C-alpha cells in the first residue's frame, strides 16, 4: 500500500551545525532511495516552533529532495517535541495538503534530547512512529527510556539510539524493511 511519511527533525540550540546538516542529508538519502515508490514525503522542523519545510503536495509537485530542503535554516531554539508531534498529527497529515487516505501514516522523528515541553501525543498514536535519539544525552537506559513515549510499540524496534550523527547514513536500511510487513 501507499505510505505517507513525515520527517520531524530537531533544530534546537543543542545540535551543532554539522549535526543539523547530517539530519538534512539523511532525509535526502532516504528520499532519493525511495523515489518512484508508494512513498510520499513531508518534512517538519521543530525547535521552539514547528515549520513545515514541505508538505506532501510540495513533494508531489517536485520530487526533488535537494530543492525541497533548499531553504531550511537551523532554528537554534528549544526542543518542543510534544507540540511538534501533535502539529504533525493535525497539520501535516491532511488531504488538503496532499495526504492520501489509503496510505500508511509513518513518522520518523530525529532528536538529540528530551522535550522541553509536555503533554501527550495521543492524537498521533495511530501513526507508525520511529524515533532516532542521538548523542551524549542517550547513554544510559534511563535517559533512552524517555523517548519510548513518542514511539510505536515495542520500543525495542521503534526507538533507535545512535551515539553519533555519522551513524545516520548506515541506518536507512532497517527502516524501510520493517515499514511494510
Image (cartoon, helix red, strand yellow):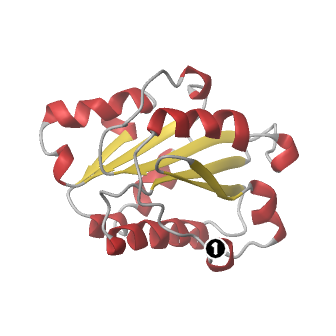
Report helix, strand or loop for mark 1: helix
Quarter in which the N terminus is drawn? top right
Residue 144 location in percent, x, y?
A: 23, 37
Which of these two is toward me, 123 or 80? 80
Residue 92 location in percent, x, y?
A: 71, 44
- Give the class, few, some or many, for how many residues have Cα within 10 Å of label 1's Cα (few <14, many ≥20): many
| Left or right: residue 122 compared with residue 97 | left
Q: Which residue is mark 1?
A: 65
Q: Is residue 121 above or below residue 163?
A: above
| Left or right: residue 73 compared with residue 150 | right
| Left or right: residue 180 compared with residue 95 | left
| Left or right: residue 17 compared with residue 43 | left
Residue 154 in view of the camera: no
Q: Quadrant of residue 122?
A: top right
| Residue positioned 62% across, 75% down in the render | 71
Residue 115 location in percent, x, y?
A: 37, 37
Which of these two is toward me, 117 or 41? 117
Marker count (numbered): 1
| Residue positioned 56% across, 25% down in the render | 125
Q: Quadrant of residue 69?
A: bottom right
Residue 154 location in percent, x, y?
A: 37, 27
Residue 16 in view of the camera: yes
Quarter in which the C terminus is drawn? top right
Extreme left residue here? 140
| Residue positioned 13% across, 45% down in the render | 139
Amino acid at each position: 500500500g501507499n505510505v505517507d511519511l513525515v520527517f520531524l527533525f530537531d533544530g534546537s540550540m543543542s545540535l551543532q551545525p554539522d549535526e543539523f546538516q547530517k539530519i538534512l542529508d539523511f532525509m535526502k538519502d532516504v528520499m532519493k532511495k525511495l523515489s518512484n515508490t508508494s512513498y510520499q514525503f513531508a518534512a517538519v522542523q521543530f525547535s521552539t516552533s514547528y515549520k513545515t519545510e514541505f508538505d506532501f503536495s510540495d513533494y508531489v509537485k517536485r520530487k526533488d529532495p535537494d530543492a525541497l530542503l533548499k531553504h531550511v535554516k537551523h532554528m537554534l531554539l528549544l526542543t518542543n517535541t510534544f507540540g511538534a508531534i501533535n502539529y504533525v498529527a493535525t497539520e501535516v497529515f491532511r488531504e488538503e495538503l496532499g495526504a492520501r487516505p489509503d496510505a500508511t501514516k509513518v513518522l520518523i522523528i530525529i532528536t538529540d534530547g528530551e522535550a522541553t515541553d509536555s503533554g501527550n501525543i495521543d492524537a498521533a498514536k495511530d501513526i507508525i512512529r520511529y524515533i532516532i535519539g542521538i548523542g551524549k544525552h542517550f547513554q544510559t537506559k534511563e535517559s533512552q527510556e524517555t523517548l519510548h513515549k513518542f514511539a510505536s510499540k515495542p520500543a525495542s524496534e521503534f526507538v533507535k539510539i545512535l551515539d553519533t550523527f555519522e551513524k545516520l547514513k548506515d541506518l536507512f536500511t532497517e527502516l524501510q524493511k520493517k515499514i511494510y510487513v
